[PDB]
Length: 78
Image (tube, rainbow, N blue to C red; front, side, top):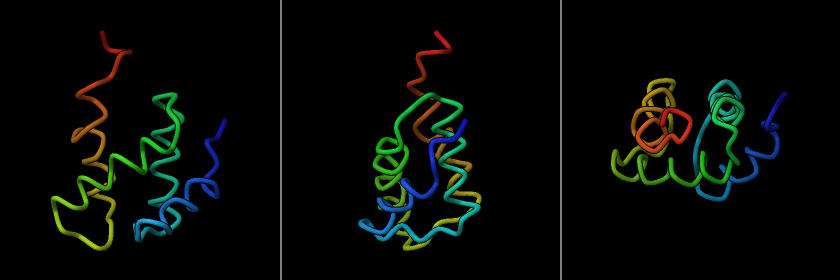
């Protein structure tokens, strides 16, 4: 069951979040694993990209985003 990469990609184009399809699908995997809407996965990632100053994203940035924000607040682990 997917969160739909084509709906997530429409938000990345507003904020200038440069990703390939393999990095767009990485946030779809988080939306599906966490049971969470993509406006969180796109919106909270901007703060991380601002703090690193990076204009483009990597397989390392979207891997670290799980530990930088998502695992810190998870309700399923309580």
